[PDB]
Amino acid sequence: DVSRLFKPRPPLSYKRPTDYPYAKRQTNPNITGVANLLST
Amino acid sequence: MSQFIYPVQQQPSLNHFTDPNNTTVFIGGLSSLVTEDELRAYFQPFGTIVYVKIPVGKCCGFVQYVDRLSAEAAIAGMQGFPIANSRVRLSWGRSAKQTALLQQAMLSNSLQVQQQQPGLQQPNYGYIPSSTCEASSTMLPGCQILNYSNPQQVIMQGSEAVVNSTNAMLNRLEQGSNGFMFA
Amino acid sequence: MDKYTALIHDENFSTLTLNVSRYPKSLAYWEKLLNYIVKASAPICKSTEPQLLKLIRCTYSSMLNEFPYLENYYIDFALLEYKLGNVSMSHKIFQRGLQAFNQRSLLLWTSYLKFCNNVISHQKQLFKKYETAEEYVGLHFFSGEFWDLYLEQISSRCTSSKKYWNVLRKILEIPLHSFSKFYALWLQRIDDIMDLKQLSQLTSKDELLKKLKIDINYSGRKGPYLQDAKKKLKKITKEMYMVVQYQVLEIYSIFESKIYINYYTSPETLVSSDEIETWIKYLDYTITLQTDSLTHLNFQRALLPLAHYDLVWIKYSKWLINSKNDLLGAKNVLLMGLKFSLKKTEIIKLLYSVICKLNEYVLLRNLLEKIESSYSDNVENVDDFEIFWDYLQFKTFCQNSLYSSRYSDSQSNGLLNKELFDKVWKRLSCKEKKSGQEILLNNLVQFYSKDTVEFVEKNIFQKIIEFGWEYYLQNGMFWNCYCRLIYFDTSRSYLDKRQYIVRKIWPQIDKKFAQSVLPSLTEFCESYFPEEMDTLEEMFT
Amino acid sequence: MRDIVFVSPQLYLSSQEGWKSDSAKSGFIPILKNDLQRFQDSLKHIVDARNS
RNA sequence: ACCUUAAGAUAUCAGAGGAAAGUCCUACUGAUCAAACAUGCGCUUCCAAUAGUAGAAGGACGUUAAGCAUUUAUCAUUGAACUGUUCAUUGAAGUCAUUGAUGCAAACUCCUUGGUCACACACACAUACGGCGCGGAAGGCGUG
């Protein structure tokens, strides 16, 4: 009766991820420069 | 108070049918044209035999095997098999001394008490029940290390037993056709 | 100096590995070597030497290939591989172990499912594994643990709570060792029902209305009516329990109480006669019950203690032949028992006959070639006579079927073809070392035609007569065979054959062999030649 | 592998050709390649008995 | 045996008074805010057949079901034939699954939930519809 009450839930099922991988996560690169706006 | 209890039961009073150590087979309905040798020939290949008797004029005999397995196989296989044109009904029985004791005890109607047949004193390792022998060994499990003499002593089975069995089979097939034995 | 090289340059490793390689079938040296190789790796972890791990894996695999029936080492190897971090190879090990038992092994199934629960984590696949396992090993007498695992998994995962009823209903009828626990579960779970509609979990509405006279949609006062339904259901459960208790108590009282050993120990073990007798009786009882799954399970369960005895292999093949009519099944069972049994003589004979029956003669020819090659093509000099005799019979059958007859009247040359006659005469040349001389002579006699008897006499009996081998010359059964060969000939007239015997054969024997040749010769004389008996006894004074 | 080779006493005593291999098959026992000569010498008397 | 501490504050602006410049305070006074508690709005939405064997909302980690349609099951080295293809060998990893996965769709079975309230079995309505029975749930707004 020591740990007969804290029976955990069954292992969580696996679902294919719908997000980007931790290696591919990034913000926007190739942020274009600010000098072109000043002219026009 | 627990809801699970071990089962308990009453004993069936040890007659010849309810004895697990009983090995003798009571053959009834013999035609009186059969003798001890022919009956032994009938009941030999199911196992080794301690004794075979046919009371004179009582139209019934007894076969005392060594193995309970042999006796059960004999009863299961030889049932209704006609010896000397008369069908035969097999059932369990008792010995000769026990038969005489029971007859005197029911003539005197005193007790009618039976005694259980002796056991083999387990554990036994050499023997394989329901096995036949007629006449080195590494004592490996596959073979049969020990066996019973054909009538009684105990002999260690060898590799030449298969040769001897075929030799005797051919001998009794040649001679038995000429007619020196009905067995 | 690394741990692996230090181990491999240790002297004890050479001695243990040599004992193992010298005595492959003892398993004491196997287990000692495995304990040593495991213990020499003090930490078992993911960072220990890859070479050492590969060595441990190969040692375990070699032992499991040598002894296929060790459940505990399958489990231990799979658990060690699980500890090493990868579970795919653990699954492969468990599946290989299950296949080694033909999927019927309670301990392996229990440990495999206990490991599987933590790992698979996919409801459909896990439950399909459970359904597959129950089909093979569910009817075991000691199958309480497997059903406990199944019930706890269902109660933990399922939320509809109908599969629990549908599985406990099946469990209620199997004669298990611990049927009482499941009956108590059933009684409590029926006792905790609280409304009429939940009785539809038990059976169908039409069935309840028609058999038990219980109406689920009964509207009104439902307290006493639900109590009536509970009483009727408990009566039905009591009758089910009566049947199951009778079955289980009979089985335990007769058979299961006498069996003490249920585990495969080693090829060097001996099993007791009482246990053999009770195993045979129990197998017969199971066959009589006529349940195919239960019979297969009981045979595979009986193979564990007495695998190396071959009587259970023979009995299993006989059952598959004459009760299920499955000759391919019998061939497979005997072919598998060929690996295990230590006698192999009766199994080889029965396998020969079965393969002849299935009209598969190419496999028969291949088996004959293999058994001849196993003795370096010198099977004619084998110490054990039975293997040679069976091989000679079936090789003669194949030779007759393959080569056209070289004698008249389509009298097929059985043992008179130069391929087999060479072997027969080579065995006859030993003359005291072997055991089947008389059997070979007597089985060579039977030909019964003019040219065939002429050939047999001239090649075997005349040649031995001229060589004068004392062992055969003083053995009266040889003279009986010669006289019987001549006398049963269908070509000679009676006067010709009597003349031939009396004036040729008998004078050819020496008088100093009288005290040994007289019994069999007189036995033949009394049976066939009562008139010539006077001549015999006069000449043999 | 390294410093370990598989030998099969049954196939060796049956005078066949594939008694030694580097693949882990059924009926194969590991052995040290340095010590294969002593493995052969251990079975010498039994193989001579079979030959005679 | 190890441990003994972040520091501040508790609606807000404006006006009158008391202890040049802040500084503090006022069971002081206005206005705003926030909280609690009462209390209302012709406020807004929702509250299940019995005149019947139903239905609504949400589930199923339920069955049919191997449903109907698609699609997947290693890499390196060496030898051989071959016009890329096939067979074998050594090494390296390797979630289980293929009765799976994914796409589509339907039937069935079952669980939880609710005023299963009262009066009615009714000819209404253009300003379109007495929102003119008692409660309950949830919000919106107003007053004290």
Image (tube, grey):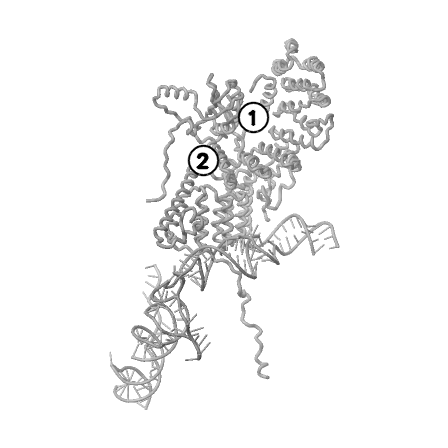
User: Chain ID for label 1?
Assistant: B
Q: Viewed as shown, does residue C35 lie left or right of C527?
A: left
How far from the left and from the top, in percent, is residue C121? 49, 55
For marks 2 and 1, give the one nearer the viewer: 2
Q: Secondary structure at mark 1?
A: helix
Label 1 crowd bin: few (<14), some (14–19), many (20+), radius 10 Å: some
Q: Which residue is mark 2?
A: C255
Question: For the residue marked with disc 1, what is the amino acid?
Answer: Ala
Q: Secondary structure at mark 2?
A: helix
Q: Which residue is mark 1?
A: B161
Q: Decide if residue C105 is in sight here.
A: yes
Camera-side residue of B151 and C281: C281
Is label 2 in contact with label 1 (beta carbons under 8 Å)? no
How far from the left and from the top, in percent, is residue C20? 55, 40
Q: Residue at x 54, y 38 (%)?
A: C25
The image quadrant where one finds the C terminus of chain C is top right
Q: Viewed as shown, does residue E80 lie left or right of D26?
A: right
Q: CA distance from mark 2 to mark 1?
A: 32 Å
Camera-side residue of C256 and E18: C256
Q: Viewed as shown, does residue C467 lie left or right of E48?
A: right
